[PDB]
Image (cartoon, coloured by chain):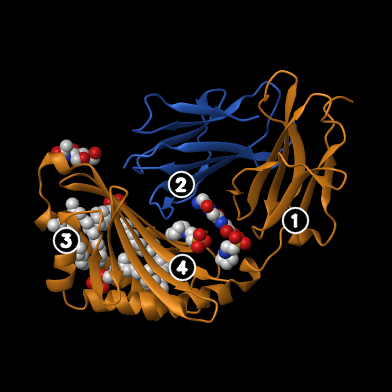
Chain colours: A blue, B orange
Amino acid sequence: IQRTPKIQVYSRHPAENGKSNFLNCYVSGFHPSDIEVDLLKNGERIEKVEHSDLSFSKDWSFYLLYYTEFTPTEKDEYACRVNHVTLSQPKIVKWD
Amino acid sequence: EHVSFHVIQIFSFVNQSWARGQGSGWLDELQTHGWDSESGTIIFLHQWSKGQFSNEELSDLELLFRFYLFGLTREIQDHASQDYSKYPFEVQVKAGCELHSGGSPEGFFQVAFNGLDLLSFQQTTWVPSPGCGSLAQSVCHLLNHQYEGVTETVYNLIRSTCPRFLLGLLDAGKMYVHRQVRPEAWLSSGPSPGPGRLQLVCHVSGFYPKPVWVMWMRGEQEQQGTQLGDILPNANGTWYLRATLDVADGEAAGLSCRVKHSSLEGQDIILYWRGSL
Ligand SMILES: CCCCCCC[C@H](C)CCC[C@H](C)CCC[C@@H](C)CCC[C@H](C)CCC[C@H](C)CCCOP(=O)(O)O
Ligand SMILES: *[C@@H]1O[C@H](CO)[C@@H](O)[C@H](O)[C@H]1NC(C)=O
Ligand SMILES: NCC(=O)NCC(=O)NCC(=O)O
Ligand SMILES: O=S(=O)([O-])CC[NH2+]C1CCCCC1
Ligand SMILES: O=S(=O)([O-])CC[NH2+]C1CCCCC1
Ligand SMILES: O=S(=O)([O-])CC[NH2+]C1CCCCC1
Ligand SMILES: CCCCCCCCCCCC
Ligand SMILES: CCCCCCCCCCCC
């Protein structure tokens, strides 16, 4: 049983340029729990992130919430990057 | 209004002599406790995480958990097949209780191995999982036969201690678990459904409790195509929901997102789709 991570990226608040916000990345439905989740700013990893403790659903697949406080600007692209043993390549989901 | 408390454990053996462990306590979907492996102690995540238990009961529980982890590692070594074939592997334990409407407690203690059911604890015996095979039976034989109070301690923990603590938690956390948090909503354009088509997205973020009503509307007519995403967690215990609607270009005008939530007290959030002055 090896299930691949679903990645959902969303902000806590509407994207206002120059206003503080939270970028969430919810990664769920993966197994085994070994995983590399990073929030990216301009393709570079964000160190100042938080994440929930590993948890899992009734089907035993795992889920993690990541979030980082950020200030979106026009030039800055943010993303959530997940590497997993079920992935041939790191999956990168951008934020709108 | 069924409520539940789970202690979960995840541990992965990367090889025969090296394993990672992780543990937490969850009031429904709210994490209330973590575990500090490097002192073997409970992390109380909220002011109220002691949930009406004394420091003595809680430190007894900690001691219990440590004796449990010690026995677990000792036994995993002494009965590991030891061949590199069976590694890496991952065990998940979900133990706890569910309190039903009338007050009837239900205990559970389920284990998975590599994300498949391994065994559970029913009444007073370790039931191996049907779909699984001989590993399940081996572990159940060890737990049913070659142990002492292990099985009875699990019984009391999940049948008596756990509902007691669950209720203490809800009570101590009453101001948190009974709170109301007003969502905010905003509109965006989602991934284009196609040429001449728009994806209207209504984001509702920051509501708690979880029940929420979101619809795209044309006046009072609910748009049938509306899709509700998963209700996603925010940090600090609120929820997020996207309600989306694909519409023809030229049919977007007039559509609005309507949000009802217990915290809004009749005053629904209404946002009209704009996109072009
Ligand atoms: C390295 C990984 C370790 C993970 C350990 C997980 C521990 C959690 C996170 C501690 C916080 C939980 C919270 C304080 C819960 C309160 C304690 C009571 C109310 C729950 C009891 C019921 C529980 C769900 C069962 C857990 C049983 C345990 C896993 C097995 C012990 C039996 O073994 P033993 O023979 O030593 O008695
Ligand atoms: C077991 O895995 C751990 C962690 O990956 C590593 O430190 C250790 O060297 C490994 N032992 C082996 C491969 O025999
Ligand atoms: N760990 C991801 C997740 O689902 N977290 C749930 C959470 O934080 N819930 C807070 C609440 O239910 O009030
Ligand atoms: O900090 S840590 O080294 O990841 C804690 C690991 N202890 C668990 C892993 C082996 C199974 C039972 C206990
Ligand atoms: O009833 S419920 O709100 O969906 C409980 C969900 N809690 C999850 C995390 C802790 C272990 C169980 C799965
Ligand atoms: O509305 S809801 O958020 O889906 C209910 C889930 N349980 C909550 C209330 C009691 C435990 C903390 C979280
Ligand atoms: C503290 C008691 C823990 C007992 C669990 C032991 C599991 C060993 C698995 C061996 C497979 C044959
Ligand atoms: C390869 C060994 C599999 C080990 C499964 C351990 C299950 C632990 C159950 C703990 C109940 C007290």
Disc 3 is placed on an element classified as helix
Give the residue at x 14% y 39%: B85
Chain of the residue where label 1 is placed in the rendered structure: B
Residue behind mark 2 = A63
Q: In this view, does A28 lie to the left or right of B14?
A: right
Q: Which mark is residue A33?
A: none
Determine the CA span between mark 4 and mark 1: 26 Å
Camera-near label (3 vs 1) is: 3
Label 4 is placed on what type of residue?
Answer: Phe
Disc 4 is placed on an element classified as strand
Camera-near label (3 vs 4) is: 3
Q: Can residue B38 be seen in this view?
A: no
Determine the CA span between mark 3 and mark 4: 27 Å
Q: Residue B5 carries which label?
A: 4
**Mark 4 lies within 8 Å of ligand 1 (Cβ measured):** yes
Q: In this view, does B65 lie above or below A6?
A: below
